Length: 317
Length: 319
Ligand SMILES: [Mg+2]
Image (cartoon, rainbow over all chains, first blue to last red; front, side):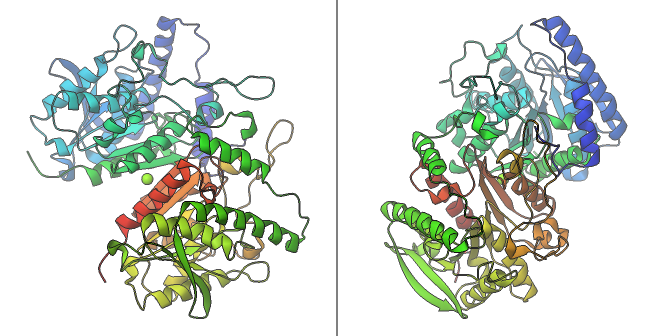
């Protein structure tokens, strides 16, 4: 095995051990226990968020979808008066509602100085694809009443990255204008692939062990029975959906199981002539930036804010 | 170690073939016999050049610019009208010790042919006979000469492996000399920074695993070319210097996903972004260091297109 990456701050090295301590025990398919565990995990990261960042949050309903609107406590910045971001939370498509959503929205709202509308989308296994696309699209449609499409960004982490990419295709199915920019962080509209799922240990490899091929679909209940050929569901595997993608930020830890898929999606975006940016944080795991107590998380929030700042329009609307 | 993984499932059949040939073509131990080592890599580079000539149609001329030997590589069809007032400078790889001649054409030919541009590949001074900053001086002298014919904004500089390191160092040397900075650079599989992070362990540059506890990595590049240069020389290690990083031109960083240089390139890209520099990073999952010297796979053609696309979007056009 490996020492921690020698690029990491002392604070990140501490976070790595806290991450290890916070890892889930085996649930053996007990969704109730699993949801309760991750509820507490997300509530814990929320407390850390609130210590670092000063925000105000309000509940709203937009086109019959529950959202939380997250803003810097004293107001959005003049630079971002006519912009908004939609956040789509992660949580394996089965949890993350409420505190998980605030944990992704608060650091970006506070770092960029922008309104973040985080969507309480329908979750699996009770709901299945394309429920979350429909929900995010309904919110987007409502926000178009106030903000130019060029000035709206959509981002999310892990499952939320996947749903962000699927929401783009659903928006185009509905005949609405595409968003100004997206962030598909730690996940996008494509299966995990390449080397990283083996290195990250999501699939066993090594002495005494037969390493299997990887799946061509995402294994989640959310995607049960959706075909590989559905370009709306898996747009980053489709040369057709890819060309219509808006400017995209892809960001992951270097040890994240999603990283090989993101580097491929970035190559495909570039060949399609789509503006895209990829950043990797060596040594860090999946969805590392839910832990705000390290310079590397603040840096990630700065890269997300800078990508939206440089790609979204400014004009009212 | 990667040997426990299957080939990346992203790879074309052609690339899986290349990876088997790459492993089979790996060098034996030379034990400080530099003459034998150079002969082995002369053969390797000649072999790749044969492959390049099958795929691409170019013409090469020798020239001397400011007392430095170059080869000027152009598409056999001619430079596109779009690229009439552009030029790229190539700085070859080869561990700072070999690669001169055929190794330089192996890097220049695919880019000249793919972009439709003239590439000047520099026959710079090698280690261990010559030491830093000899290669920076050579590349700067070439750049100086090309400024007589092309606007700085229309000149790119790129190189692979040791040549990616030297391209970054040449940029700081050009600045030191008071010349205008180049329009864009490609620091491929290497830049002005030591190797760092996880990737040198994963690639086996430092022995790694069960029962053998991994040593720290050096904060310096180990090559004889760089021996005695301090970590604090910002001109030698610019991507660890906030000052030289801010002055970098738009930069492409590209590597194989299994390349020992990956982790350093991802950090350099974060630093360039924080410094406000236009940079772009691409990683080819499953592929090793300097993978695009083997042209017989879709992934290599795809790399050449990304390099051509980066320069086509970042360099100026006007005479
Ligand atoms: Mg990029």
